[PDB]
Length: 273
Image (cartoon, rainbow, N blue to C red; front, side, top):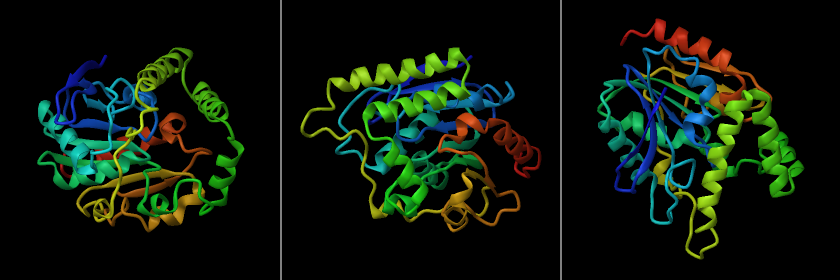
């Protein structure tokens, strides 16, 4: 199983789950309230026990503390993650992220003295989509999906239905225990005037691509192919791939057989291993 630990950072305590082993698979979630280990259970459960695991919950999500993020920058969050990296023994790692976790991931791989062996992205947020806004008409299909989900209940029920289809009843309930715990803590602060639930991105955060030296495996729904082909998440590495699959944004829930297949292939052929 995974060891739970609140690790100290300049941003205050950060919830982590950890398993020894080298290289270490480091997980970062998208925007949401799910705890990261729960969020990525279908990938974590499938990795060989010999492989390390580190999951990290962002502030105001999962079991990390709630706090105002108004004065927090991506650099601050990246520095906190790097402190967390230094807290554990692994010497090399792969980053596996969903959605907004892509932004931190790019800086981490560019700044960490530990060796990155690979990036695994499940619809990582691009500067392009970010500038436009997820669900902003750029993609008519995203605009229609968002428009269908009128109410908070609709949006919640959509996630509930989706997760229900892709997790065991046990991992489903656990996933939602984290969501509900997070939302409960958020009730105390989210209606306060100055409160910002997440750090704001700036232009200075959009100037980093992935090194040519690091293989990248990106998974995305087919309609986003061009965006990703032109994106900061792809490079010319002989092992880098763009895999088109899935019917929704949560590929780390539903496409883990395919993800594991690509991951195993990446590791078996990596000249730094």
